[PDB]
Image (cartoon, coloured by chain):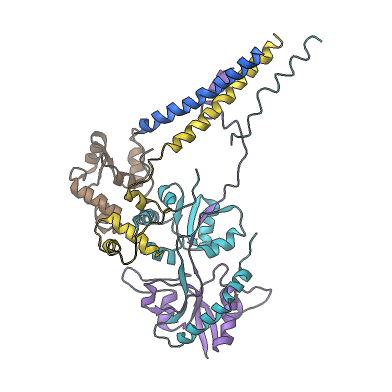
Chain colours: A yellow, B blue, C cyan, D brown, E purple
Amino acid sequence: LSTRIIGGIWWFFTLIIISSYTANLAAFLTVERMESPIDSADDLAKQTKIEYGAVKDGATMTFFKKSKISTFEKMWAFMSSKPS
Amino acid sequence: STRIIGGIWWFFTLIIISSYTANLAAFLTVERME
Amino acid sequence: SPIDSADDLAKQTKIEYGAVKDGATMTFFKKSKISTFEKMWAFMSSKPSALVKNNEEGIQRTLTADYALLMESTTIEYITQRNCNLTQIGGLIDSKGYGIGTPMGSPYRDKITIAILQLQEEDKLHIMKEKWWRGSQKIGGIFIVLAAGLVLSVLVAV
Amino acid sequence: SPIDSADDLAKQTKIEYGAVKDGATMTFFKKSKISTFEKMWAFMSSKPSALVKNNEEGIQRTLTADYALLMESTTIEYITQRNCNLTQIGGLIDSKGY
Amino acid sequence: NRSLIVTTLLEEPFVMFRKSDRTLYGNDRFEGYCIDLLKELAHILGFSYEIRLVEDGKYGAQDDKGQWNGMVKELIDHKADLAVAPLTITHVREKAIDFSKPFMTLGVSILYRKPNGTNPSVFSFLNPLSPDIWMYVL
């Protein structure tokens, strides 16, 4: 019993530490499975990390200069903000 | 020999379901918010 | 997971932010015509008090409140290099030129047009820039459980 | 969380929002050249039922319809000083000469 | 040339005070990055100056009607004929005064207060459950 009070608290504490990584792993993969990933062009208009544009002497350059879809217009205001 | 073989194997049974709980819950949680 | 960009600052409405009034920041914020910054313009329009009148006032906003401040890097450089209770977040947005003030129709500015490129090759602006800018959980806390249980069994019988 | 600001009402479609007539903010939304208020005033143009005419009409519409009532903040105090079923949502939109 | 009157405003570390235990006036009130850069170009392009601060303390811009005030109005009214400052080249500010070439071109940075770290703890772990329940386990 003097050692029955030793081992059971170790069982009580080794049960503390095993579910700790189960949620450290699980919510980590859940954030990894939060990703759709980003495909659609409105989401590229939401992000600022990926540089994006077209070729000079291209029609779609002038078309996004001419575009009335405001998703195109804000991606054109991106490309106006960054000439690269 | 058997108490350490069963100890490490039960310790690996402690390993494996923590992974499958990671497999199952992250599956059902994206559709829980979806 | 922390913030070091512009879109995730456009996400959060949890940190107060404005600018120095009659500032070229705010003069461009009324000219900001992309909707990620148009909504931060709707923020700053919804908060005339987040707008400051003094950079030193916005210093006391960030010192006394959880206050993001979006000004030019030069003073943010010189003060955060000299104040360590304030953190530098991410990078810049743009780069706008700093003109030298002449009234309109000044032909003496043609001489001013020359001497700037004089100082550009001779690199004097960076020489003074180095002259005038000067630099400076639950992971570990669990230790309350098991260590006492090993000592009680010693002083019982023997 | 989903509503902590006035723009949260401009993002949702369920909770209506309007103002008592002789309303300065109805005028101010026409005055507001910031476009999120312009969308909130195209809301109130599209929603005649959201725009109310006197005090208890907006009180009842907040209780009956899915409706947030827009009102001055120490008046929001003074009513909710006595009306306890409420909760003030968001902060100010402005400070204004009175 | 003449003493070209300079409207300005004190910035960090652009235009700063000159400080001592005695009296200092005008050009001798003020130093900094811009002022000691101005002392170089006074030898370069051959002019003198008077430094004046701006009142309203700001750049100043067009109002609701469209009227300049502050720094721009000084160069409009010719009560100042220079402005030694990082006067940001803004396309509306080109319409009452003319800019020269930029000496510095920098961008908008992000100021935020620093949390200065923290320590690990288990009183934090007592918190996702109600703290009376942790004693109810006992």
Quadrant in which the C terminus of chain D is drawn: bottom left
Residue C16 percent coordinates (x, y): 45, 51
Q: Is residue E81 above or below residue E90?
A: below
E39 or C153, nearer to the observer? C153
Which residue is painted at 24% across and 57% down in the image? D30
Q: Nearer the viewer, residue D93 or B20?
A: B20
Residue A22 appears at what percent x and percent y? 52, 28
Up the image or down, C58 lies above or below A29; here it is below
Q: How many marks?
A: 0
Identify the residue shown where x is 24% and y is 41%. Answer: D58
A39 shown above or below A84: above
| Residue E43 appears anywhere in the view | yes
List the single residue furthest toward the front: B1
Q: Quick check: can you spot residue D93?
A: no
C124 relative position to D65: left or right: right
Q: Residue furthest bottom?
A: E1
Q: Position of residue C51 (x, y in %)?
A: 43, 58
Figure quadrant of the N terminus of chain D: top left
Query: Going 43% across and 74% down the picture, which residue do you hit?
Result: E70
The quarter holding residue A10 reads: top right
Quarter assignment of residue D69: top left
Residue D26 location, x and y as percent?
Answer: 24, 52
